[PDB]
Image (tube, rainbow over the protein chains, first blue to last red):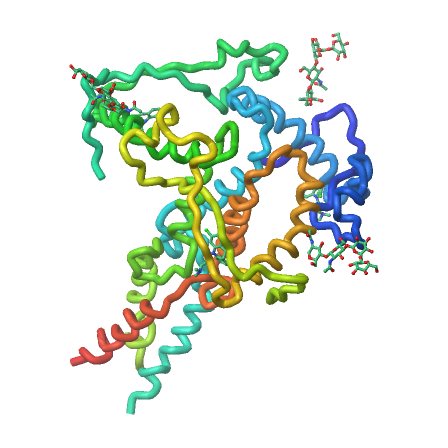
Length: 130
Length: 130
Length: 130
Ligand SMILES: *[C@@H]1O[C@H](CO)[C@@H](O[C@@H]2O[C@H](CO)[C@@H](O[C@@H]3O[C@H](CO[C@H]4O[C@H](CO)[C@@H](O)[C@H](O)[C@@H]4O)[C@@H](O)[C@H](O)[C@@H]3O)[C@H](O)[C@H]2NC(C)=O)[C@H](O)[C@H]1NC(C)=O
Ligand SMILES: *[C@@H]1O[C@H](CO)[C@@H](O[C@@H]2O[C@H](CO)[C@@H](O[C@@H]3O[C@H](CO[C@H]4O[C@H](CO)[C@@H](O)[C@H](O)[C@@H]4O)[C@@H](O)[C@H](O)[C@@H]3O)[C@H](O)[C@H]2NC(C)=O)[C@H](O)[C@H]1NC(C)=O
Ligand SMILES: *[C@@H]1O[C@H](CO)[C@@H](O[C@@H]2O[C@H](CO)[C@@H](O[C@@H]3O[C@H](CO[C@H]4O[C@H](CO)[C@@H](O)[C@H](O)[C@@H]4O)[C@@H](O)[C@H](O)[C@@H]3O)[C@H](O)[C@H]2NC(C)=O)[C@H](O)[C@H]1NC(C)=O
Ligand SMILES: CN(C)CCCN1c2ccccc2CCc2ccc(Cl)cc21
Ligand SMILES: CN(C)CCCN1c2ccccc2CCc2ccc(Cl)cc21
Ligand SMILES: CN(C)CCCN1c2ccccc2CCc2ccc(Cl)cc21
């Protein structure tokens, strides 16, 4: 489904913070003893509403809440870190969880450039037929 | 291996409880503040011994214990939530962890309907040969 | 990249300890109540510097530290058990995260023994052509 922002307002710009997990450390800064404290590990950036992605993202986070809260109600884990990894596994299982029937709509195998490996190899034997 | 129930008795019916993780919530019931308490999140059902699955399941849980206890002895995690996700990964790695040699017994790729895409395409060029 | 041990010294032998997760238990030893205490769950072994793997491994662990410490700085998990499982997922996603274009350098599908299934099947119809 498409996402329809139905909020009273939308801040169209996203001034965000996150961590850089693979930081190009300078000298000893990667050593915990010498590195930044908890407050100084963040990077920042600014994103504008190109393609309406910011207003759509606000609505998406909004619409995600019901399913996320129901998932949290059903789990006994106190802190859940595994949602994205489980999504990655389900991505793979949806495509590769069974036999891949080539040309099938649910089999992600492209034999396009391989048919030209053999349709140029029709003149293998039918062209050279002295 | 097949499962042979070797227990003194078997309750052939399984009156079970579980959680519905994607619940079709009614109104505000998905909001933790308004929703059910810990005791009211469960659904119930009843399963009979069709195909002997209940008596087999009791024996399976029984026979699983040794390996499960040895796994728990070797882990340092206090609470283990990852067994099923690891099983899913190993499912994928067993089939897709290496090169898939088509027609091989360990490669789950079916080219059956794709050979008829090219065996009906023998009359491509051998039929139309004026 | 290759690994170049740049340490002051290298102990070329690895006297290691680990756990056997699938232990061939003898009798009741798998039962926690009867089994070994925390100090008696370990197996041991000895590895020599064949192919320079021990000296390389010491350097690898050394060189891994910066990236590992930066990963730990960016996570909010108190104890991280998921690095290897995430590596396995990324292994699969790198090969199977998109459409597999056969003969492509990033598609791990081998049609070698399947082309002989059809190149011996050129004499299907071109040999038997009465
Ligand atoms: C996702 O986005 C939705 C849209 O922004 C959010 O919807 C909000 O949902 C809550 C309920 O969960 C509503 O709060 C209720 O408000 C009503 C109406 O209050 C009105 O009453 C007076 C008198 O009639 C009226 O003059 C005012 O205009 C008030 O607005 C109360 O009766 C309820 O008791 C309850 O307080 C919000 O109104 C509703 N917003 C909108 C714009 O529909 C939703 O909460 C978001 N989800 C998350 C997880 O944040
Ligand atoms: C999986 O299913 C198995 C089968 O139901 C369970 O097997 C049970 O395993 C325990 C040991 O772990 C046994 O308990 C032992 O019982 C013996 C014999 O007691 C008998 O002794 C008197 C006098 O000879 C006899 O008259 C009675 O009939 C008694 O039965 C004791 O000597 C031991 O000290 C120990 O208590 C069970 O007997 C055994 N059951 C069966 C039916 O074989 C197994 O426990 C299940 N696994 C899990 C994890 O639940
Ligand atoms: C991975 O392996 C590397 C190589 O074994 C390790 O490199 C070590 O890194 C630390 C810094 O993190 C260095 O410690 C520094 O030492 C210098 C120099 O001390 C020298 O000074 C006197 C006077 O000049 C000299 O006579 C001596 O020979 C001393 O060696 C100090 O100035 C610093 O303050 C700091 O103490 C090590 O020297 C360095 N070792 C080598 C062999 O380069 C690295 O630590 C390993 N990584 C991990 C995570 O273990
Ligand atoms: C510039 N765009 C091409 C890529 C936008 C990246 N992006 C993203 C990706 C898909 C949909 C919405 C959004 C905008 C939100 C957001 C927030 C954080 C990060 Cl780290 C990326 C991110
Ligand atoms: C009706 N059967 C076709 C499907 C049975 C579902 N099932 C199951 C699946 C494989 C083998 C044994 C069992 C019976 C035990 C059990 C328990 C809970 C649930 Cl949520 C399903 C479940
Ligand atoms: C005998 N070698 C063929 C296999 C070595 C096994 N190995 C290993 C594998 C790849 C590279 C370095 C090392 C040596 C270190 C080490 C440590 C523990 C274990 Cl459990 C295996 C292990």
